[PDB]
Every structure is written in C-alpha cells, then in structure tokens.
Length: 257
Length: 261
Picture 1 (cartoon, rainbow over the protein chains, first blue to last red):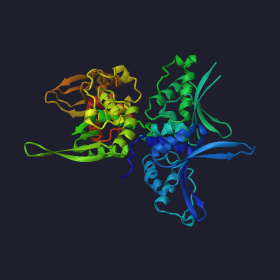
Picture 2: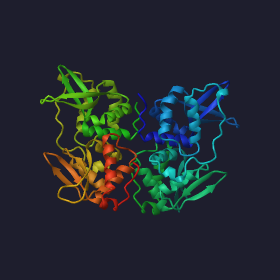
Picture 3: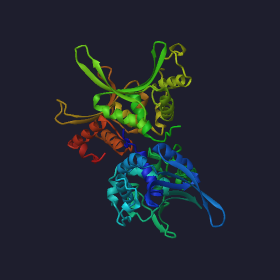
C-alpha cells in the first residue's frame, strides 16, 4: 500500500529537516547522488535514531572531524540515499507538509528530477535557490500544520537561556526568513521581541514575562513534542524559571512534559 | 523497540477504547488473542488508515445475515499475530494507557500474552472490575488526554443540527455516548469548560449533551485547534455541522467559526 500521511509528527519532521537538514542532488563522477540528510551534535544522536525509527528508513552514522589543532570533533548524521525509499516515504511526507521557506524550492527540484529517474549528471538542469520568499506570512498562518512544523523547527533552531537579578529569554535563530519569523511572532502573540545581528547571526529574542509565558504554554500544550537535547534544555529552563521570582509568580510553570 | 513518541497512537487508543476490544477468547483448547474494532461501512477507509499507521493487521467486510432475510454490512480491523501484538500493540498501550475500566482488559490481555499462555485451561478467571481505574483528576493529569479525546470523539461523539417541531429555529448540539464512564465524562466537561451539559437515557442511552452557544463554541475550537484530527466519517459529520452552524444566527454571531479544519 501507500504511506499514510495524516500524522502531524511528519510535519514536525519537516520542520526539523528544514531547520538543520538538507535535500540535495550532487555530482558523483558522471552519476548523481540524491540525499535527504541531517547532521547534529552528539547530544542529539538518540534523536536521530528516533527519526530513523519513525521514518522506517535511513542510516545513523558518526563522523569524525579532523580539526586544525590536531583534535577531533564529533557529529552524528542521519540520511536516506535509496531512490525507492525517497520516492516512497520522503516524497509523500514533503508533498503533504511542504517546507515554509524558499528551501521548499530545493524540494521541488529534488522531486522533479528524482521522479524522472535522472541519473547521469549531464541530463541534470541548472539550479539556484530563488531569493524570493515562496510564502507570505499570511500563507504560513493559513497552513493548518504550522504549530507542528514549529516544534520541529524549534527543536533545531530555538534556544532557551537563563542569565544573570535573573532573566529568561527565548530566541529563534533566523537565516533571513522574516515571513516565518513574523508568522511566529504573530501566532504566538509575542510583543517584546528584539531582533539581533551578532556576526551575521541574526536571531529573534524576547525576555518579557508574558512572552515567556506564551512560549512555555504553547510548547507545553502542544501534543507534538521536543524529542532530543532541545527537550532537556527546555525542561532545565523550566526548572530554573521556577526559582526566578518574577516569573514563577506570574504564572503556573507546568511540572509535566 | 517501537518508537512511541507519536501522539497519533494516543488517538488510536482513544478510538479502540470507544469502538474496539482487546480480548483473549477460547477456540476449543487453544486461545485467540485479538485487538479488534468494528465500524459501519462509512468508515472502511478509516480502518485502512489505522492498518497503514500501525503497519500490521487486516481489514475485512462482514455480512450479518439478519432474520428478516436481509444482509447488513460492517467492516472490521483486527490483529491476531502474537508477535505483532507483543511488538507493536503492547508498547502503544503501555505508552498511552486507556482511561476507563477497559484498561483492566488490557492488563489482563498483556499479562497472559507475555507469560505466553496458550491454553484456556491455564487462563486465570477474569471479570472487568466495576470500580473506575482513574479518577477525574487522574484523567486531567494525563498529558495525552487531548489526543485520546479526538480518537474517542471519532468513535463516540455526535454533531447534530436540526429544527425541533416545537421551536421555530434550528439548534446545535454536541453529544458523547456514555457507557459507565462518568469520571471520564466529568473530565471532558471540565477540560472543555462545558457548563450547560445535560444527561440522557433514551433506552439506556446514557450520554452527555449540550446546545448552549458557549459550550458549542468551546467544542468547535478545541476540535479545530488540535493538531490531532478526526480521520473518518466523524470528520465529514464535523465539517457538515460547521457549514450549517454558520447559518444559525445565535451561534454565528457569538464567535468566528473556522473555515479551514
């Protein structure tokens, strides 16, 4: 039979791969390599096995990076290279819950070529990701799987931090995709968000007490959950937030997640 | 080991708890273990979705030969393979436990299956406890209640629009079929902030009903905002309900009825 895709966690997966993964076609001599992949830190290796498990396809590997200094850094990776697996599992998932940013174009190209069985590099047309945003902030807000996509995006690109009395902030690393950032600001009713640019490291942040409450309650009330390290950071964040007077009193920081 | 992080499995448990069964039955000296569910033909596509989501099981059509000479139809989905039950079904129900007394059927089913009981003679006696397993507060404390609720609504809720012959205009009502689950019914009333519900008993038809504009508002928004959706006929009934609800002045003026589910 075919892949049933009415399950929201597949939207969470798209969010995760849109944030930190990739779906490309590359030149392997006179042949082509099609690959859906994602690389994360060792702290998220279990998350990659979870992905492998949910998708039923793929391979989890560990890569050793030879640093300049002579040391070795580690990363873990999940990828799918089997053409039939891509056509039967991945295509249907992304068709059902397409990516939100311009990265979506990478998908259409990947898909068009894959389904046409292009295998020699010389039969492959030229491609450069468009600079125009595929969707407007309102097209995003009209998508009924936004909140699910968002947990996967947060899993990959959000950050919870408590710093020195004390203050709490929620940030989302952006890679010039304001339409998505505005959809998030709106959907979550975040008011005191300040944008930044630290070494072209553009991000969106907020520390106000109500904004934090809104973020915590959206994350907490969503049936779609953080699965890897990001979940631990979140739970540690709450653990801390409970000790900060102005926050723990302003609302009921939940104890179950 | 099966990954059970997907809340749609809680929806599945919610659906089976409402219209399904998980039992051990005799077959002479042997024992049949079965997770099963029977629905009307209108939901045959839904059974196929369950099948593809669980990755196991079989869908069949049953012909009930009535005494009047007519053949009535129903469709069914079931899992009988011991390995499939141990490796898929057990982990799901362990992760997202049923909420009513029916949960006892599960524990019983699971203890025997794991102990590898094969003969009816080795089967200890069993009668589903009468006292509820959970309290309303225990229910409200489960973090997967809202996902379970959709599967349970898929099976036991009912959206109806109609014009009684004693009132000039149509009324909107949401009802949930009862079955000795008042602790669960109270958790729903509480969780959905329902304030004008009434109870029915039309031919032992214990159920909960509400027609108040605010109650209906709460139900429609809960359903529409949930990432976990109605997948079968119930969904179609839900969508036809909204389309009509839009034409009833008192409900339409009270709140913004969603146009996309």
